[PDB]
Amino acid sequence: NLREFVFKNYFKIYSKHTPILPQGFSALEPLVD
Amino acid sequence: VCGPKKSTNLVKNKCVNFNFNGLTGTGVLTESNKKFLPFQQFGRDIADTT
Image 1 (tube, helix red, strand yellow):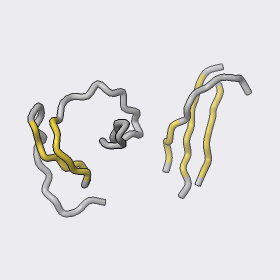
Image 2 (cartoon, chains in turn purple, green; image 1 turned 45 degrees about the vertical axis):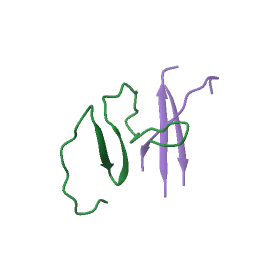
Image 3 (cartoon, chains in turn yellow, blue; image 1 turned 180 degrees about the vertical axis):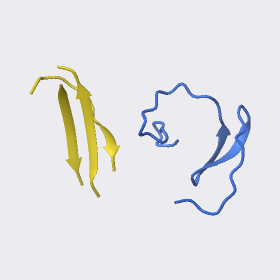
Image 4 (spheres, chains in turn yellow, orange; image 1 turned 90 degrees about the horizontal axis):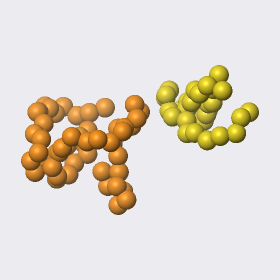
C-alpha cells in the first residue's frame, strides 16, 4: 500500500491511497481541515 | 456561517435570479454531468466565473 500525504499550514491534510518510492503521477485531495 | 434568510425551492430549466450561500447571478439552472469531487463546492470557467 502506497499512502501519500500533504501536511501544510490553519492546518490542512491532503492525501491519496493507491496499490503498489515508485515513479508515477497523481494528485492528492483535501480530507481534513 | 449564513444570515437569517428563509430558503426556497429551486426552479429548473428557466431563466432565474439565484443565490447560493451568498453567491449570486442570473442564468438557467440545469442538471450537470460534471464529475465533482467530494470536497468541491462549485466550478469555474476560463473567465474565472461560476
